[PDB]
Image: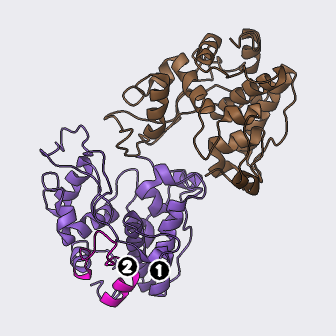
Chain colours: A purple, B brown
Amino acid sequence: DISKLISRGTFDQMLKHRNDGACPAKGFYTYDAFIAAAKAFPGFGTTGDDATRKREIAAFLGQTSHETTGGWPSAPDGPYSWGYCFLREKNPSSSYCSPSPTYPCAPGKQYYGRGPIQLSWNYNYGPCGKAIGVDLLNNPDLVATDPVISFKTALWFWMTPQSPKPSCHNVITGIWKPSAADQSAGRVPGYGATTNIINGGLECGQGWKPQVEDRIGFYKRYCDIFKVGYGNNLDCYNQRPFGS
Amino acid sequence: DISKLISRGTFDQMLKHRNDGACPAKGFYTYDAFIAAAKAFPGFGTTGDDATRKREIAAFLGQTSHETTGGWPSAPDGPYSWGYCFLREKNPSSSYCSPSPTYPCAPGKQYYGRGPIQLSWNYNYGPCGKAIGVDLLNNPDLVATDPVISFKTALWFWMTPQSPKPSCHNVITGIWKPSAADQSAGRVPGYGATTNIINGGLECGQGWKPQVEDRIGFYKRYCDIFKVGYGNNLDCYNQRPFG
């Protein structure tokens, strides 16, 4: 179980300020919910040598910390201590409903960002819910009211390949082998390629971006706390985005 | 219109291989479509002294030539005669969909590179379509099947500032006033800043790139045909990419 590799103390040290009065998700994101969710995803934080398992947990908590960050440059303990500050997308101006024979939008329900990966759109809530065994198409706000389901949605995203994207899991553990195509595109194994899978269309292949800097700051601080090296290729600044 | 500044004959000498059998865009990119597209963008090729107007057309055609090049080192008449050879991105391997509530991806549509600037992504087809009065989210392939819309997407890109980036138009005409940040970053007026606007993340501030040399080769050849100087700062090798 990953509970040996990441203790309650280490988890609370990494996510130091998530329960500060200013954070809307205060009290929601629990160590027990993270550990219970990880059990549902064999291989998560249990793949590779100890250093690689810690890099995987740091990378998962890093990327999710970015998606939910309340950080700012002069934040107490730095901006990479303010992961998991929010739960629901701020001021959504869409239902995130998209034409689909397979994933009909449920009446009165919205598919705005929820939980540690800010899961969005009926066509993501559908296959995610199917995968974890919950009807998230018809009960989307479970991602913001059930903290085990919340973490499961983010682990579903992390562990699930989506052609032509490999899984973040396979990238960070070194299971993923770049294609000749990938190598020409500058898509090399490491933390950078997890950013590319998450939001490469907007964030990768356009040089320095404060968003990608933020994803890296979290990953580095968590690796520092775990006492493991970052590995290589942390940015995607020269990576062509993975396809959709 | 700009037909007096760039003739059919000059346009065809510049883009002399685009109608070869070896070019997928054979017969598509017409002088008439170019001139018609230009009229929709007041100021394009009509801003500045005669040599500045010609540098603008040379720069626009040079950058779009690079985006669509069929060139290679041993090409007939050299690589800088092979602009406008391609219409659609080759083997996109992507629908080029970045989920957006603002510019949503239409089911069954792809936003891979099309036309002279190789317009890509729902988040570009969206605002471009809105600007030129065409629904490019539901009909993105209009950029590869209608030559006027095709040129209009490239002119939209050229003429449209995207803060903190100025328009290519204001850079090449010398209207652009570099910011304090730009000055610190080594971003200086001239053709090089237009390369920075178009693809600076991958091409600028990181040493010699064959892609940058290709953009400059087209621009120089079109300036030579117009009988005008290139101006300064043609590469972006010491320019930090725009934010």
In the image shown, does B86 or B232 lie closer to the viewer? B232
Residue sitting at the far front: A21
Please give the range of residues in magenta.
A8-32
Secondary structure beneath label 2 = loop
Q: Amino acid at mark 2?
A: His
Q: Amino acid at mark 1?
A: Pro
Query: Dot 2 falls on which chain?
Result: A
Q: Is residue A14 magenta?
A: yes
Q: Is residue B115 magenta?
A: no
Location of mark 1 (residue): A76
In the image shown, does A40 or A204 lie closer to the viewer? A204
Looking at the picture, how far across and down is residue A58, in whole percent? 42, 76
Location of mark 2 (residue): A17
Asked whether, in this view, residue B47 is left or right of residue B90, the answer is right
Q: Along the polypeptide, which appears first: circle 2 or circle 1? A: 2
Residue drawn at (41%, 85%), measured in percent from left and top? A50
Looking at the picture, how far across and down is residue B129, in whole percent? 46, 28
Residue drawn at (58%, 22%), measured in percent from left and top? B151
Please say if A82 is above or below B222.
below
**Does the CB distance between marks 2 and 1 fall below 8 Å?**
yes
Residue A126 visible in the picture: yes
Residue drawn at (33%, 57%), measured in percent from left and top? A90
Please say if A126 is above or below A51.
above
Magenta stretch, main secondary structure, is loop
Classify residue B116 by image quadrant: top right
